[PDB]
Length: 304
Length: 304
Ligand SMILES: O=C(NCCc1ccncc1)NC1CCCCC1
Ligand SMILES: O=C(NCCc1ccncc1)NC1CCCCC1
Image (spheres, rainbow over the protein chains, first blue to last red):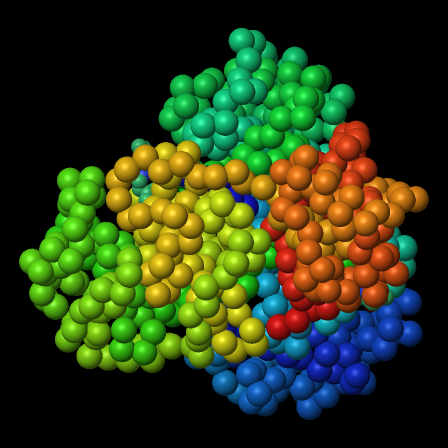
């Protein structure tokens, strides 16, 4: 009972965090096997950062200009390469704490945990979603670059995010672990505007099911709707369209609560049209969209 | 930039979690040095649970009736004792992953991280506060008993909470690591009502400072107030009274923002009197009270 914004336990990722120094820039790296992953902008002098040519800047850099410190022990760099916007530093020592892992590129609406780090050391963990405009609304200060986002499935860490950038609007931009930015952003100190931050409709539905499972039912109404009618309303309210793929993924929550997905859609529709009237659902005065259907099933069934 | 509900990294506590079985009841234990801490109700048959005499039930229990499994390796129990509502199982092996630690009893309004565990295995981490009625609003299913709440200061884990009980209202009750319940609750299957869940005023103020630091300023007004006038309003709105001790602890946030504590009090007063008018602060449509002043300073200054 109770429904909390919950992060994956951070221990497996804590054991991968190192400090990368190049010149006067220190940020965080991810040490997996004998490779340290970090943002390539580690090589920039924030005067470079205005219009960097990373290939050209990298010519001036050797293995020994990359300082990699794990705990307070130095790793020997025996190779370096650039993959998109990340540097891969080959070290002479495989991380003895390497978990089973994958690199996954997630879709907008997918949630993950961030281990916020400074100087290769963890400060905190929180739950995030990839916004539909491919930003995340994180908590990141100077020195946090290289901090990673991840999901855990039993023993396997899926790394989905590395932190690169703060947009001038104070939202956050970064890469998958192959160094490809989510969204159109570039690792450059240039004004870059984010698109519309729409609500992740499928996630709101999942969280309305979590609320029903936990006893919060006041918002359940006598209406149903169709996919097309609901989507007209979603559009008007800057909600992502709902697809049959979203309806399918919600099946187990529909199943447990006996509330048809389109019925829950008609309940959400009325919440958009009438607002909450000063009421709360699961202790929130607005509709939470950073729980996936998978996250609700996980938390509601006690998965480890 | 950005302000997130943030938990301490969970790795140091993950390495302490074990599974305790007694009879047919399995829950979680905390293994620190050569001692495993768990809720004493592990020895109850939920028929015992109606009116248990723990001393009497413990007479029927030997070292070998307590099954303690760490990973999938069994610990040999060489002693057991009861301290208030917890059992202390002496094992023959000191936990090699024991962090530096303390047991602390926290006050209502203090925040901590919970590592929710099932069968000695972590499922997730979230941030909590000890409510002023000495409940916490957690996320806990059957098998979660023994899950702990904690704070970290650099390398030292302060354990403040062990999970014992779900009240019939779906809020949560438990002990410090000396086995003393927060609040008046007893480890018994008997209807136990929680008192008024008032808002932690000092924490709301800290989070209003965090909002100002992060650019959310719309709620700042032209008024100030006094401690006595503010407290009249707090009382009317089921907010905890504000003391000079709360004002003192807020000093650094006052200092950075140049907003006198009593000025921020007058801003909160107007938010209580006028509500948010459909506006948000730090992405919330209500006033968050699960950030302490210490938590705001920590997150806003990047402490590891
Ligand atoms: O340097 C910065 N932001 C750029 C650094 C950064 C990088 C990735 N994520 C978040 C932040 N802010 C400073 C802090 C102190 C006050 C004046 C602005
Ligand atoms: O057994 C229970 N609660 C008691 C167990 C418990 C203990 C500590 N925290 C939280 C929960 N609920 C069951 C679950 C399945 C549906 C019917 C009620």
